[PDB]
Image 1 (spheres, chains in turn green, purple):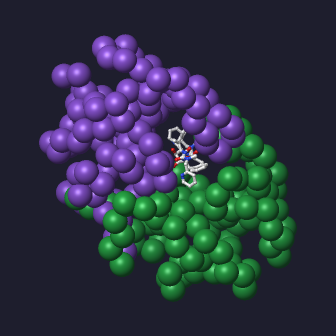
Image 2 (spheres, helix red, strand yellow; image 1 turned 30 degrees about the vertical axis):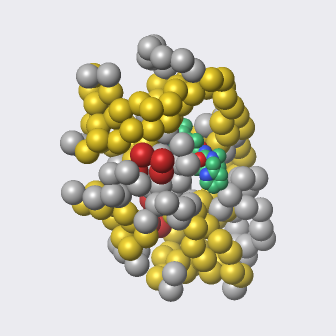
Amino acid sequence: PQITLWQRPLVTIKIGGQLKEALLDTGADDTVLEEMSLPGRWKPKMIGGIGGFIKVRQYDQILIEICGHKAIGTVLVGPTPVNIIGRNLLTQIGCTLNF
Amino acid sequence: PQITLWQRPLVTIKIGGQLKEALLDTGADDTVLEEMSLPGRWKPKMIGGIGGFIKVRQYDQILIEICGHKAIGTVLVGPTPVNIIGRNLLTQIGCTLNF
Ligand SMILES: CC(C)[C@H](NC(=O)N(C)Cc1ccccn1)C(=O)N[C@@H](Cc1ccccc1)[C@H](O)[C@H](O)[C@H](Cc1ccccc1)NC(=O)[C@@H](NC(=O)N(C)Cc1ccccn1)C(C)C
């Protein structure tokens, strides 16, 4: 699709067999989701942004589907205000910025 | 122009007749710039991000030029690591997300 930015660019993703909403975020390097249980082993990590650092669980090679497009990559889970899709998966689905 | 997302989407902006670099960010509602001393009146404000909140000063009606395109609006100034161009100015330059 072509998404304009008059509203937050929130879409539906599918992950773990669950449906969620997430923000398409060109200003994020990584993908951060709210607390959930995913199958798999995970490692503790830290990530930062405005306000500071949070602790997250890192899951690799996770299948996610973003507007019907498949991506397979690293997902961090932790206490984010919002589900964020970052550049690690935006590139996999062929996302660009245009103006 | 079309910007790919392999790297962070950093572009040149002109503000106050000075050039800076800034991140095009579809996940920011607001525009946040590094500390600098603009003339003008300001309001104090708090904005949040992944790790919590920071204090900023709010300036309205600022002209920024982004890759040749002008935009005019509210800019928040404070102790950010990176200059962030948010949706309030992105919409004005006709910027879209495409995949
Ligand atoms: C999500 C996280 C993994 C990401 N971090 C990240 O990419 N890092 C640390 C790598 C890095 C280092 C140096 C330079 C560039 N990038 C991040 O926070 N990115 C920030 C940019 C940044 C980078 C480093 C330090 C400081 C800032 C980027 O601005 C994101 O788009 C971020 C995403 C987000 C959105 C909502 C709530 C939490 C996080 N937006 C924001 O932090 C903005 N907030 C915002 O727009 N809010 C709170 C309103 C809102 C609410 C709900 C939904 C959308 N918007 C502020 C910049 C204004």
